[PDB]
Length: 417
Image (cartoon, rainbow, N blue to C red; front, side, top):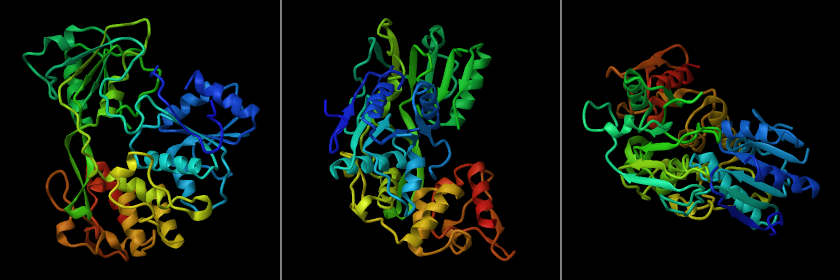
């Protein structure tokens, strides 16, 4: 009942299925004239807020926050302004929608918002059906759900899975990779089905690798779940970032994938098919340390140190405050992540070293074991600073910059300029 009181932290575990409650809690924020911050996990959810808030006086920051008692923005848009030594904003209420996403900016924002609550500067409200620290693969739903443990193919099949296409309800299918989704998509369309592939009108199939691109608009009665995903994992005693998979997903991630169906109280019998078990052993995933780096470098009133939120403090391998940088170090760290589209972990390695954004030498002073290949198997090479064609070796290896042709291409454009 004291949601909007400074010092209060409140988790709201509404059944899935932004359009009803959030407009109301913002209204009382307006009547109380409390400076409110509304955080969204994705640009999709942020756009749905624009429609849901049309009768409200809310400032949306769809690109930057460089300047109305309610502010609405994405987690990343908040994290990156906090990386600058700038004017602190006394947000008295902080509301986070879908406070369960596990990208580093989302995690660090939870610890940031949770810190302002403990510091008595803000009231913090987290909204998610799967709060952090919950590990239940089958939580409550509005309508009853049919759970089925069964073998689900990852590649197209010519025998033994009649039940998939024999069901006619609109279906969402979570697959390990976009490559698998694209391959599967063509095989389902040659089978006569309508397919839509979500990536960076009702189809018979919607294929995606996560729930990030899915708004509340999506209408689906059945979910197939490979329950796997590739992840950026820390390897080699934590001095390299490698991509590994297909790995198991956590119980909350499977609960969120399953949460796409069962949203109607009137409709029972929605079906969720899965095979793989889940796993919570993910402390070696790089996103926790990347969340620490970000949070241990976001501006806070008083310059104080904050741990990650709740159970997410157990997952990070460092200790609160450990990844803080000097301001001159940090501005390269902020500039490299924001405008050069480089992984958070890698950008922190250059800032701890002391190099500068326009200097691209570190792309070259690396050992040959750090050399990057291509899809055809050859070793790529590009222009070093000064026009010298010198070989491409990162001083710190982060396999995210060479995961596909699109990655190392744009990583080369970073090396050349």
